[PDB]
Image (tube, rainbow, N blue to C red):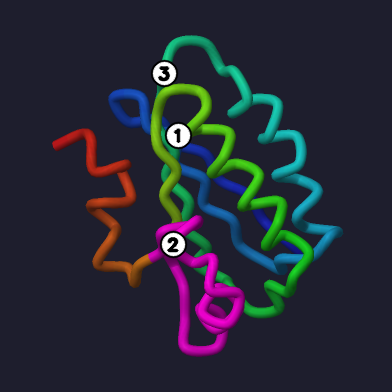
Amino acid sequence: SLGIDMNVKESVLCIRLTGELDHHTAETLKQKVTQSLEKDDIRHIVLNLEDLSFMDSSGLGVILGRYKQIKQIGGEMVVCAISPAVKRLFDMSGLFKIIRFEQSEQQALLTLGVAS
């Protein structure tokens, strides 16, 4: 069980994932890695899971891989749609700053704080 959504805004590729966040679901994004690795010019990312439940330490790294992917590309990596029982993953890892997360409110900053 897991969804997937993608949207482009000015250059920001919104990725609305709905389902689970495990090595199984984190796989889907696995492919998004190569895509984000070098899409072309310098687009933007926009992560946001509306159905964030499981989300273990499986995709945690799969998502972190992107951060160091969109950054090394020449853009920025953003992610939102956290929770009081999901942000703890990055809150405990203390690497949250490496994922720079927010809380819906980022819906705007999600655009990569670079677009409207």
Task: Indicate left or right for 107 with 26 as reference.
Answer: left
Counting other residues with Cα less than 10 Å from the Cα at mark 1, is it few (<14), some (14-19), or many (20 or more)?
Answer: some
**Which quarter of the figure has residue 7?**
top left
Q: Which residue is mark 1?
A: 13
Q: Earlier in the sequence, mark 2 or mark 1?
A: 1
Q: Quadrant of the N terminus?
A: bottom right
Residue at which label 3 appears: 42
Report the quarter where the C terminus lies: top left
Provide the secondary structure element on which disc 1 rests: strand
From this view, report whether residue 73 is shown above or below residue 15.
above
Q: Residue 78's spot in the image, x, y percent?
A: 41, 49
In the image, is residue 82 above or below residue 69? Answer: below
Q: Which residue is mark 2?
A: 97
Identify the residue at horizontal 36%, vertical 24% (top origin).
11
Q: Quadrant of residue 17?
A: bottom right
The answer to if 98 sits in the magenta stretch is yes
Which amino acid, by three-letter code, is at mark 2? Lys
The structure residue drawn at horizontal position 78% and vertical position 64%, both measured from the top left corner, is 58
Q: Residue furthest right?
A: 24
